[PDB]
Amino acid sequence: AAPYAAKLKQTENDLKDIEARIKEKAGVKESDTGLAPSHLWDIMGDRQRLGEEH
Amino acid sequence: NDKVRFIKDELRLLQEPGSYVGEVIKIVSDKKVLVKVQPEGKYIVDVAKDI
Amino acid sequence: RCKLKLLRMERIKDHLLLEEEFVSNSEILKPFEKKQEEEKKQLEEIRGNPLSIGTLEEIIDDDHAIVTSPTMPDYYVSILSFVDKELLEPGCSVLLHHKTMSIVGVLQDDADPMVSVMKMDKSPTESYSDIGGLESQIQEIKESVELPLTHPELYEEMGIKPPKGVILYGAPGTGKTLLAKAVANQTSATFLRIVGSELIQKYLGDGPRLCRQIFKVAGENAPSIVFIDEIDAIGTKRYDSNSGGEREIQRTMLELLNQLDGFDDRGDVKVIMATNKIETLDPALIRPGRIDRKILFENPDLSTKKKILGIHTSKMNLSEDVNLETLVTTKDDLSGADIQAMCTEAGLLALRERRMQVTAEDFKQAKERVMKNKVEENLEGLYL
Ligand SMILES: Nc1ncnc2c1ncn2[C@@H]1O[C@H](COP(=O)(O)OP(=O)(O)OP(=O)(O)O)[C@@H](O)[C@H]1O
């Protein structure tokens, strides 16, 4: 099945890149809640975090 | 000497704060692990330099 | 050369891409060094470790909330530091601070073993014209399922609301099953598929929460196409009769009317229903405008079955011996699942030989096995 069989292996070898790429893309990934205006909320909510009312 | 300084050093080693068994539910890529403690609930908690 | 041409471009590009991203991991952090680098330090100290999972019952608009933790104790926490209150709202799983509990952010969300049955992990490898023939009762399923996603333009000219829903009905084996999975390959939008045998449960109250869910997820991740495969299964399947029965069937039906439609104003949830017990449904289900164009399928005619049988014999080894047209002669207003089982059974004759060839003899023999099935749960012989 020579003409087809060669491509079939080469497809498997290709797949091995797709897994590796998912792991490198996820190695350096960041995540947020609420971004830029709640950087400001850190200044304020850190003074109020020291107290007890929670 | 190997003997007596094995006893004296095991008295230190036996003293713990409690060291648990957890299971990993899933990872998060902020470099933290969501671990469900087997009796207790879930806590996202940082990892050591060996893992 | 015809496979290779495809491969040569596409592989080399996936190899480069991969390599690119390795050198690049480091490079992400380089345009900053105090512009964002510093910001990251500030957020972290606030967070500390462990971040304790809670469940947010409700918010109060004074920068606080009441959490109930799965560890028992409720806490009157404060929504402070690195959090929007627009990413808060009932059902959230939250990160609490391990001294005084403040909500530092929401990152955690947890999938159900029922949204796992609903949500699919595939994109269908088969596409359209794998049961093809009856290919004019298929533009009632691609002018009202495929097309208002693909073009808004056409239905803007005429104005008004664009299509909504289809009920597929007909004989069994006449392609209904494959129709639904063949439009989901073409559109490429969230394909939910739920069996109706799972909508019937042996426990009450959970029945309605399941049916109420399918369209709520559906509207959330819109566009969505929800295949309800088999809604003929709601009156024929039922376990016990004391947590089954009438009551459980009536309630799931009632629920399903609010979802479609109803008052919800949920997302796009085109609906595809397969059935053949269409009169075990409500008049507010087979109501127009939750069904728009409805599609009837009957058994193919003689010249249609020639379209069907040439799709199926392309995948098989052939000879000059094979003759399609006399296989057509024998069958008379039978399903294309019958015709699909003769070709599947013909390679069963090849397998049985251990010969790699398929001949006219292999197709005629399995035609006799296919006709044995039909007339031998019969025992009248000639119509008494
Ligand atoms: N026109 C056709 N061309 C190719 N395959 C066909 C055709 N009609 C039906 N089939 C095949 O027959 C099998 C069963 O059909 P499918 O599930 O698509 O439909 P259906 O009418 O709901 O029948 P059932 O629900 O009893 O299987 C599938 O493998 C399908 O692809």
Image (cartoon, rainbow, N blue to C red):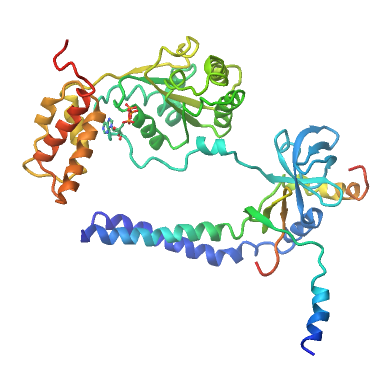
Please state, as top left, top right, bottom left or bottom right, where the N terminus of chain A lies in the image.
Answer: bottom left
Q: In the rendering, at what x and y percent does residue C353 appear?
A: 14, 48
Residue found at x 80% / y 71%: B14
The residue most toward the bottom is B1
Q: How many marks?
A: 0
Instruction: Answer above or below: position of A36 versus C137.
Output: below
Q: In the rendering, at what x and y percent does residue C275 appear?
A: 39, 21
Residue found at x 51% / y 32%: C223
Q: In the rendering, at what x and y percent does residue B19 appear?
A: 75, 62
Q: In the rendering, at what x and y percent does residue C45 appear?
A: 80, 57
Q: From the viewer's perspective, is C255 left or right of A16?
A: right
Residue found at x 43% / y 29%: C151
Q: From the viewer's perspective, is C107 left or right of C158?
A: right
Residue found at x 50% / y 11%: C284
Res. C249 in view:
no
Q: From the viewer's perspective, is A21 left or right of C332?
A: right
Q: From the viewer's perspective, is C238 left or right of C345?
A: right
Please state, as top left, top right, bottom left or bottom right, where the C terminus of chain A lies in the image.
Answer: top right
Instruction: Answer above or below: position of C1 versus C371.
Output: below
> Dividing the image into four equal quarters, which quarter contains ligand 1?
top left
Residue C125 image-quadrant placement? top left
Res. C268 in view:
yes
The residue most toward the left is C321
Q: Nearer the viewer, residue B18 or C114?
A: B18
Q: Nearer the viewer, residue C231 or C109?
A: C231
